[PDB]
Image (cartoon, rainbow, N blue to C red):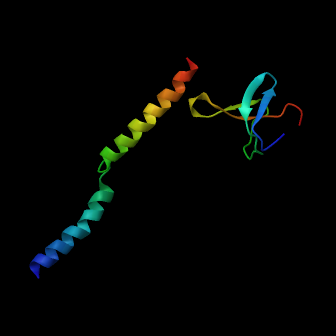
Amino acid sequence: KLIANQFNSAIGKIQDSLSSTPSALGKLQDVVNHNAQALNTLVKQLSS
Amino acid sequence: VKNKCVNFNFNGLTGTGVLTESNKKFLPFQQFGRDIADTTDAVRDPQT
């Protein structure tokens, strides 16, 4: 019973920890931002 | 001419593409429209 209760509490706290952290999902966002930045600079360099 | 891939020349502004009725509010002193990366996106009809 104690182990099950501890597991339930930890799983419940996981979602709040993910929501509260500002840079928890940083790596995926950096990947997306790098791809977008590369495309943007490629498009903008046509004006040179 | 609308809804066809057309070669348009608006007061010297030359381009190729299809035209669609707009829903954005241009200011009376603005005649061009540019999106990010300086791509032409909207234009006012000089007559109507």
Residue closer to the observer: B17 or B27: B17
Q: Residue at x 14, y 78 (%)?
A: A4
Residue A40: x, y in percent?
49, 32
Q: Is residue A32 left or right of residue B46?
A: left
> Hey, which residue is sitting farthest front in the picture?
B5
Residue A6: x, y in percent?
14, 73
Q: Is residue B4 left or right of residue A43?
A: right
Residue B25: x, y in percent?
74, 42
Quadrant of image for the N terminus of chain B = top right
> Hey, which residue is sitting farthest left in the picture?
A2
> Hey, which residue is sitting farthest bottom in the picture?
A1
Q: Is residue B2 left or right of residue A30?
A: right
Q: Residue at x 57, y 20 (%)?
A: A47
Residue closer to the observer: A28 or B23: A28
Q: What number of labels is visible?
A: 0
In this picture, is A8 found above or below B25? below
In this picture, is A17 found above or below A28? below
Quadrant of image for the C terminus of chain B = top right
Residue A19 sits in which quadrant?
Answer: bottom left
Q: Is residue A9 left or right of residue B3?
A: left
Q: Residue at x 53, y 29 (%)?
A: A43
Residue B40 sits in which quadrant?
Answer: top right
Q: Residue at x 41, y 37 (%)?
A: A35
In this picture, is B18 found above or below B38? below
> Hey, which residue is sitting farthest right in the picture?
B47
